[PDB]
Image (cartoon, rainbow, N blue to C red):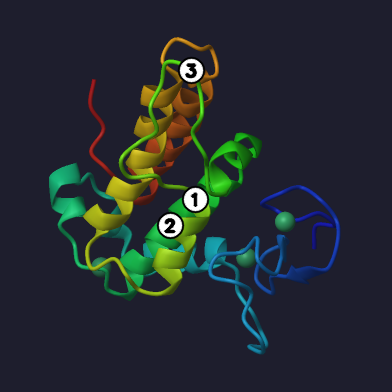
Amino acid sequence: NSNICEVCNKWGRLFCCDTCPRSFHEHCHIPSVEANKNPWSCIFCRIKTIQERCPESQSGHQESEVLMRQMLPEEQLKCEFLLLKVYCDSKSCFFASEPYYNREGSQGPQKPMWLNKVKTSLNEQMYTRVEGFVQDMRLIFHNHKEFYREDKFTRLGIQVQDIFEKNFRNIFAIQETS
Ligand SMILES: [Zn+2]
Ligand SMILES: [Zn+2]
Ligand SMILES: [Zn+2]
């Protein structure tokens, strides 16, 4: 097993996957690392099993059909994994916790959003369709772009949105286009 958390890249109290060499802090894994379960398989392993059980799940899909999918267990897991892939980027720190807005010339968003809020909402099964989760994720970056206006800090929202969008296309096997 690796000696650092796969998500935050730090050592500490780590739980080790049984089917691959990754390790995790308890609350870095999503969902949080389960109490018992021997053997235990990480989210990476669980996602790979879905693909192996249904190889055709990798054929291209339209985004509009993906978004309308109900949050059955396999789509729940895919969204958890996509959320985890965002936390994997260190720049996710800017979007993790509850923001506040007091900048000359800007007004805060009408609907603030942040990663830990999305994490709670997934844990509490508050999204009934993939679209709910994707809308809240895209709202994080849109709020940031609007608030920061011409400040160069706007670029952090572009960067982390690009990580989200690339992983969304991968995990949900969105049809490749020019
Ligand atoms: Zn960690
Ligand atoms: Zn694993
Ligand atoms: Zn199949």
Image coordinates of residue 10 in percent, x first then y, are 81, 50
Cα gap from disc 1 to disc 2, whole angstroms? 5 Å
Q: Quadrant of the C terminus?
A: top left
First in sequence, mark 2 or 3: give its number. Answer: 3
Residue 6, labelled with which disc? none
Q: Is residue 111 above or below residue 116?
A: above
Amino acid type at circle 3 is Glu
**Who's the residue at 26% across and 32% down the image?**
176
Q: Is residue 150 above or below residue 2?
A: above
- Left or right, 118 with respect to 62, comes to right
Amino acid type at circle 2 is Val
Labels 2 & 3 near each other (Cβ < 8 A): no
Residue 62 visible somewhere in the drawing: no
Image coordinates of residue 167 in percent, x first then y, are 43, 42
Image coordinates of residue 132 in percent, x first then y, are 26, 56
- Disc 3: residue Cβ within 8 A of ligand 1's nearest atom: no
**Who's the residue at 45% across and 71% down the image?**
123
Q: Which residue is mark 3?
A: 104
Secondary structure of the residue carrying tag 2 is helix
Q: Nearer the viewer, residue 50 or 119?
A: 119
Residue 118, labelled with which disc? 2
Q: Nearer the viewer, residue 116 or 131?
A: 116
| Mark 1 neighbour density, 10 Å: few (under 14) some (14–19) many (20 or more) | many
Residue 115, labelled with which disc? 1
Residue 13 visible somewhere in the drawing: yes
**Who's the residue at 39% across and 33% down the image?**
108
